[PDB]
Length: 147
Ligand SMILES: Nc1nc2c(ncn2[C@@H]2O[C@H](COP(=O)(O)O)[C@@H](O)[C@H]2O)c(=O)[nH]1
Image: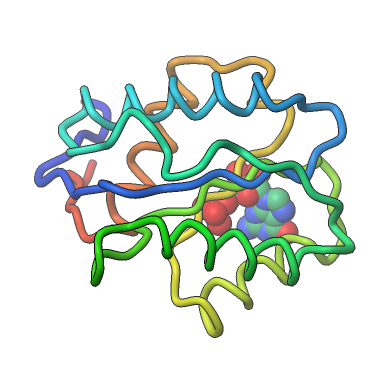
C-alpha cells in the first residue's frame, strides 16, 4: 500500500508565484492545474482556478513579490476569507530563496506554502503530483495514512 488521504483538507483560494527563469507563465499555469487536479481526485476540496494568475519574480524580490501578491489576492476575496495556499516554483539550486520564502510565509504572512523544483515542473509525473498532494493535505489540516 502507498500512502493515501484519510481526511481531505480544503483549498478554496490559492495563488502561484514563480522564481524560475526557465518557466513561462503558461507552464506554471499548467503545472498548478495538474497539481490542483491531483489534490482533488485524492480527496481534497481544491479550487481548479487560482485567485490570481501566476506571477514571475526574481529571487532578489522575494519579500516584495510575496507581500504584494498576498495583499492583492487577499483583497480580491469575499470579506473575511483568506488565501489557503501559496504554490512556489523555484530554481533547482536557489541558495537562500527557500529559507527566505519559508520565513516570510511562516512568520510575516501566516500562509501555507508548497515549494516545487523546476525539474519537477517540466516532468509533471503523476507520482510526483501524488506526493505533493499528500504534503499539501497535511499542511492545510487534512490527515494521511501511515505505512
Ligand atoms: N527541505 C528543503 N527543500 C528544498 C530546498 N530548496 C528547494 N527545496 C525543494 O522544496 C521541496 C519541499 O518544499 P516544501 O514542502 O518544504 O514547501 C523539496 O521537494 C525540494 O525539492 C531546501 O533548501 N530545503
